[PDB]
Image: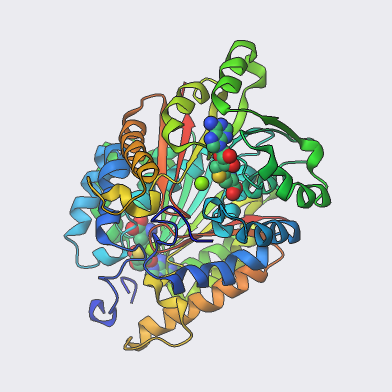
Length: 240
Length: 236
Ligand SMILES: Nc1ncnc2c1ncn2[C@@H]1O[C@H](CSCC[C@H](N)C(=O)O)[C@@H](O)[C@H]1O
Ligand SMILES: Nc1ncnc2c1ncn2[C@@H]1O[C@H](CSCC[C@H](N)C(=O)O)[C@@H](O)[C@H]1O
Ligand SMILES: [Mg+2]
Ligand SMILES: [Mg+2]
């Protein structure tokens, strides 16, 4: 992936909705008119970037923003930033004193979106950490206190590692807090045990998501809602 | 058992297999036993096309719990699938005002609501929703404003419901409109083969979607789940 080729991914032209016309209707009617001008700018630059397949889309973004506001989130973690579309979405949603821990192995991607984040006036909310996510989460587990738990986590980093992220995040997000997993329908390819013609890295991701979806549905630590928005977003709410 | 409407079996997702995967993997294992029972009786009913689907149900429940909703209003109950979802999501002392013109539909699902132990949270009003909302407006105290409203009744009246509901939910409260993609038929100016009532609803949703996207009193998110759900959050 953007982490560690573009040619290894064979489904980038697929969408989970029944037609591109329906997706374009949602974007033009309901998403783009509500998208911050700096999110638009960041999106348009990123659409030209070689890894644009990884970009969180605008209708999904407004849904993330809505969830953040409805749950009155204040402290969040963003895992897998890329050029920062979902991160800027989060920073604009949070109150003025909101705080985001943002983690990505590749800070050069973040620097593409950083001028839009800065012009949006919300960079002060963001503590960006350039690292693989798991060691950072493991260190947070050692140092965290109960009153500093996160309200919300958005997970959108190495697809094969979501299950390992989950085991840390169910302890780092507060009870009643939210953990969101991005891309859980993987272009619709999760719908079959076997699926033709994927390169090995993409098949690893597809199988990881089939296993994750089954696991999350059985996991008593959370309630879940798998939402057919974007490429599938699974919302988890921590029960205990 | 043949629907008069044209669109009932159309999916907004790209295949029935994809929808089935979501439901079987992520919805049915998480569906309360009484919701399963209520759904299974409703599937055989003449108007089963109107039933809120199980993946949408879990999404409504998640929103209610994440926003810590305590007092809600449900407009368009039918056999009660979304109503029972709401009642199970709310705390033990939660309260719902449920409104439907047809109480006979409610009584189809009421035994399952009762067995779930949540009927006490529900005040069911048999009426057209608009006069009820008009009457609420005249008596509603600011401290009694609803946390959450689910709108799923007469499609052509959604705009009229909105003008009342933006004054009956609290600041920061949620108004959800069901069916705002209308089987995907809203995506085009014209759409052949529809029942006249279906076309009325389709044009109403195209107008509503445009209006909500420009309404300064709310933020919105249109979500491609079920038949489309537009979440509104009241700003002032
Ligand atoms: N092990 C890892 N730890 C942290 N980040 C990782 C990682 N492996 C890959 N990544 C990063 O995960 C990101 C996936 S794309 C993220 C998209 C972004 N959320 C958006 O709003 O568009 C890439 O930026 C990649 O650099
Ligand atoms: N003017 C009106 N006022 C109140 N209810 C109305 C109405 N017109 C139609 N309805 C009701 O709206 C409902 C729409 S179907 C609602 C589905 C239900 N929410 C579910 O979870 O499955 C029907 O029960 C119908 O009787
Ligand atoms: Mg993603
Ligand atoms: Mg409906």
